[PDB]
Amino acid sequence: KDLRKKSELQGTALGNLKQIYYYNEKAKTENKESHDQFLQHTILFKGFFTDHSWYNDLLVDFDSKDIVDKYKGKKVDLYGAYYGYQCAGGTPNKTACMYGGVTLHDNNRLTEEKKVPINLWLDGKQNTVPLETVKTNKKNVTVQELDLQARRYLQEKYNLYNSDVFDGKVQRGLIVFATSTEPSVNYDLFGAQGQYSNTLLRIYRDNKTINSENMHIDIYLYTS
Ligand SMILES: [Zn+2]
Image (cartoon, helix red, strand yellow):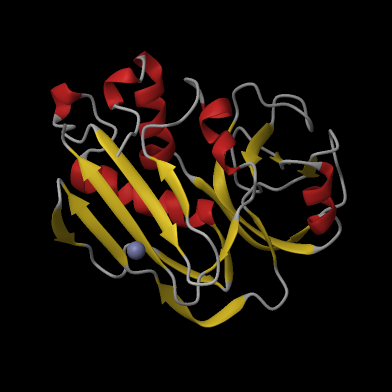
């Protein structure tokens, strides 16, 4: 183990994790481009939202200027969670923020949707997870795209981020994105930093991307 316990999470942090992974809508677009920037580790997509009530622009945060350079001016696809609190950079009051979630558009379409096999163990006992739970059309997919989908299932099925009072029985948990061609990426399900979206989502700022072709996800949940 030696993972964070949900009881170590404070007041609003648990509620906001449920907000992010269960209630909020996700930014999901194909074929966008921009060379606009706010700070040098960001890329500003002016007019990203066309139907949104409150928002207009999307400011994407990356780990460094080096990562920005790989996407700036190129045609890209986006899939990620965004927040409006403590966000600014474009149109005043109508700017939404996101960490990573950007992949190159050209030659990344798979002929058919790839269904990512999920292996799940609740207190050692294996549980069957439907194959259409986590899926993608990208050859190189951000871990964020996959994580958002997996955690929603965990919410629906296990009330992952509900307080104990509300049948939230899982206390510790881990998600592992196992690829055959590189080392695993694994997140502690209760290891987010802070209480708000602006800090809880920083885990995706590295824009970690993985080959979806022949990989799987392992999820280990514990009720104590
Ligand atoms: Zn595995």
